[PDB]
Image (tube, rainbow over all chains, first blue to last red; front, side, top):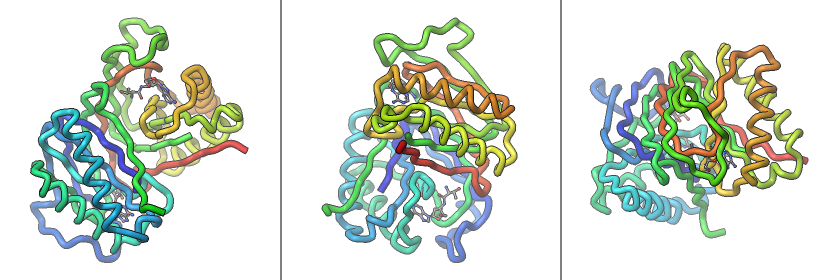
Length: 143
Length: 142
Ligand SMILES: C[C@@H](O)[C@H](N)C(=O)N[C@H]1[C@@H](O)[C@H](n2cnc3c(N)ncnc32)O[C@@H]1CO
Ligand SMILES: C[C@@H](O)[C@H](N)C(=O)N[C@H]1[C@@H](O)[C@H](n2cnc3c(N)ncnc32)O[C@@H]1CO
C-alpha cells in the first residue's frame, strides 16, 4: 500500500465518470463532496496487499492515526488514489481494504470522510505547508 | 526517483520558511507562484538516483513529456516534493537533477515553471479528474 498524507484546509471532489465496470454504488448527492481542516489520505492498494488485507488495513489505520494526532487533525478523509502506485491490487480487494481502513479510523474516534470508489474524480486541495503537512507511508504485509 | 503527475486547472504555491540549511536563494516575487492548465510534476529525488543523475533526469524528462503530450498539456510545473519517497538523495544532488528535468522539459518546447527548492511550502491544486489526469512513475538508474 502507498499512502500520501496531506494536511489540508479542505478537500473537495467531483465524480466525473465511472472508472470501473462496477464501481461502488452511490446516489446523486454523493457525486460531489467536501471536508474542511482535514488530513487527506490518498491511498493506492497494491497487489502485494492481497496477501493479507487485515494486516495492511490495521497498519494503515495505525500510521494514518499517528500522523493525524501529530498535526492535530480531527478530520481524516480516505481518498481512493489508485495511480499513486503501478502494481495495483484487484478492485474488489482494494475496495475491501479501503472499507476496513475507513471503519478502523472511525473506531479510533476521528471524524472520517471518504470519496466514492471506482470513479474518475476531480478534486481540489489546499496543503497547509507546515513541517508535517506532507508525508508518505508505504505499508505492506509482514513478508 | 518518484514522480506524481497531476493534470490540473491550476497550481498555486506559497513559500513558508526554509526547510534546509541552505535553500535556493529567492527574490520576493518567487515566494508565490501560479500556473494554469498545467501538468504538475511532484518530484522526489531518491538516494538510488545519485548513482546516475543524468540517466534518471533523461528518463524523467521523457516520461513527463510523453504524459503532457498524452493529456494535451503545453504547461508543465516542476514541484520539489521530497516526501513522495522515504529514501531521499542528498539535497545538492536533488537540486541538480530537479534543475536538469526543468531545463530538459523547456528544451522540448514546453512552457515550464518550477517552485523554489529547500522550503516548507503551502500549495493549492485542482486536478481535472479525467483519464490520465493522475499518474505516477518510479524511475531508477542502471
Ligand atoms: C481515476 C482517478 O481519478 C481516481 N482518483 C481513482 O484513483 N479511481 C480508482 C479508485 O476509485 C478505484 N481503485 C481501483 N483499484 C484501486 C486500487 N488498487 N487502489 C485504490 N483505488 C483503486 O477504482 C478507480 C479506478 O482505478
Ligand atoms: C517541505 C514541503 O512542504 C516541500 N513541498 C518540500 O518537499 N520541500 C523540500 C524540497 O524543496 C527540497 N528537497 C530536499 N530533498 C529533496 C529531494 N530528495 N527531492 C525533492 N526535493 C527535495 O528541500 C525541501 C525540504 O526537504
